[PDB]
Structure formats: structure tokens, C-alpha cells
Image (cartoon, rainbow, N blue to C red; front, top):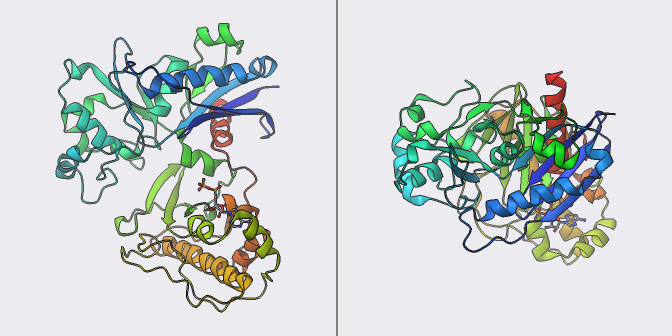
Length: 424
Ligand SMILES: Nc1ncnc2c1ncn2[C@@H]1O[C@H](COP(=O)(O)OP(=O)(O)O)[C@@H](O)[C@H]1O
């Protein structure tokens, strides 16, 4: 009977998924963000709010009437500043990939060496940059991440975030606190309270129950970031489970009982339930595949590969030099020689070599302290290549399969379900 709504506010549009408690999808949809008015000080946020209302309307009314819990994900370090009394968004949002290099020396002066906040795109750099513009009445402002802000439109209790969204402002999910080096600064007064992802905040506002026909007891739960929501969609929750994304770049995520952070390799941990999600990403993968072969060619050529035979070719497939993970070398050369005359042999070498890099990545995470990988689920454009699944199973020496779901909005709907179950 009861259903669970997840939404995903990504880089270009919004998506939703509604599930039952067994994870069966009852409704799903997508919308591109609409334009915003040039003069609108909310900027993109006005578009995001429009998309929230459009997505809600797109849910069939019979489905809305059963939705018991709502959660949503947004993009990492997309930062809004609001007045606490009026709710007015005080400036155009600082987007996930926007940088505030002006603030970075100040952040490096207060934060531990190589802390994740010490990057110009971090939420903290954005906060410090905004603070230092000396807006009148800045002491009455509050910071919200994109997901927090969209959820606050639904529940009307200002100022709450989650362990994942808050990592890039300096929140420590291991101690479940903001550290003293951050609390010692006056802009810390803008920081939101922080709860676990997928926990209840409060009931859905009456305006939404009245307008859209949600039940009066529908709750709204904290969310997460889009990258983590997409991982959650794989429904893997035990230490040693991993997801490889075979996308334009090769990104791996490993669930661990042990926290792992290493700036040499750009390795970072997020908290998930009572465990740690450990991630790293390589510049190999789909972008170099696409430079060499169309999608149609990859499918056709892969048909000719015998995935149980190893390629003798040692490649490091890259479009240009440089790697951070699993090799920390900004000058690391692409290696695609020798190139055999057979495109099938060439492709086999590339796919096998990317599997070696994937394996090397999981080995590194383990040597840095993570729970050793036991099973690898696969997402991204490369997941549909069953020959490559088999190549990877052989090279990794671990069971490999397709993740059953990979949409962030599906992962957000699992957080809605988590929060409902905890709330009952
Ligand atoms: N059969 C295939 N085998 C391996 N890779 C593939 C295959 N088909 C498409 N791709 C690769 O998938 C990449 C796109 O992956 P995707 O996860 O959809 O993209 P993005 O990272 O941009 O979100 C492309 O670079 C493409 O080369």
C-alpha cells in the first residue's frame, strides 16, 4: 500500500522514482530545468523549485495518495545562502563545479593539511567567499546545500543537512560533529544541523498535502548527494561490496568497515549507515574508448572477443597524460602501443587493461585500509558489455555482475523508505 518517493536534482534536470517497500518501481520521470528570469536573484534555484513542482505534478495522483515518505539528492557542494527569517535566497547558488579560489588561502589557514575542504570548489570555500563579501546582516543568514534547500521547501523546518552533503563544508561524520577548527570561525554560525541520510525531518507541509493529495502523515527525510544516491541504487550494503562505474571515467566505490582518506590519491570516505563508502576515480574508461570507437563499434567488435583468453597487451588507456588514482602521477603517459592491426585484438587489450586498472584501484583501497572487495557490481555505459563483464571477472578474480538499478532517484527513494521504517 505505502509508497516511497525519491527525487534526483542533477546537473541538468530533475528525476523521480516511486517504489514500494520491496523496491518495485510504480512511477518514474524526468524533467529538464526550465529557464530562469535574468533579473531573478535566486538564479538557478528558481528553476530547481519549478522542476520540483513539475516533478510532483507528474507523479500520478493515485500514486501520490500512497506516498508516505519523500527524500531527494542534489549535486555535491551546490551551495545556497538564505536569510533565516524570510527564507530569501540571498544570491545565485554556488554550483557544484564553480570555484572560489579567492577563499582558498583562508581555508588552508584554518583547516588540517590536505583536508577535503582545501579545494576551491568546496562548500567551505564558497561559504568563506560569500561571508567575505560583507553582505549587510550576514550574521542572520544560513547555509543550505541544494538537497537541503529543496527538502526545506517540503518540510518547512529550516537548517538541516546530512552526513554526505555536509562533508565538503568540513563536517566530520565519524565524530558526527563539526570540528573545532571550523566552529572557531564566525561563519560557522551559518552551518546547518546535520543528521544521517534517510532520517525523518518532519511531516510534509500541509500546502503540499492539500495541493497534490499526499497523505497527511507523509514525512520528509534527509537526502544525500547524487553520486551516493546512484551507489545506493545498487542495493549493496555489506562491507566488501563494490560498484564500478564504467562511464566516461572509471570510478570505483567500495563499502568498508574502516574509514579511508588519502589526499595523495584523492581518496575520500562518506558515511553510509554504520559503514564507510570509499571512492577513487581514474582517467581511463569511456572517454578514451569513444575517442577510438563508436558505441556501435564497441558492441560489434566485442562480439568477436573470447573473454576467457587473456590479452597479452599491457596498456594504460588515456586521452592525455596524468592520473591521480590508482597511480598518483600528473605526468603518467597514455600507453596504447603496440597497436595490433586487428581492431578486435586492440579492443580486447584496452578492455583487459582497463580491468587491470580497476583491479589495481580496489587493491589500493584495501592497502589504504578498506575492507577487501568481495563482489563488484557494474554501472555506466560499459555495464551493458557482457564480454567485458566476463573479462573483468577473470582479471579481478572476483564475481562481477550488473548493478540492478543505477539511477540516483532510485537510491533517494531507498532513503525515503529507510526514514519511514526508522520513523515507525
Ligand atoms: N558496448 C560498450 N562497451 C564498453 N563501453 C561502452 C559501450 N557502449 C558505450 N560505451 C561507453 O560508455 C561511455 C558513456 O558511459 P556513461 O556512463 O553513459 O557516461 P557518463 O560518464 O558521461 O555519464 C561512453 O564513453 C562509451 O564509450
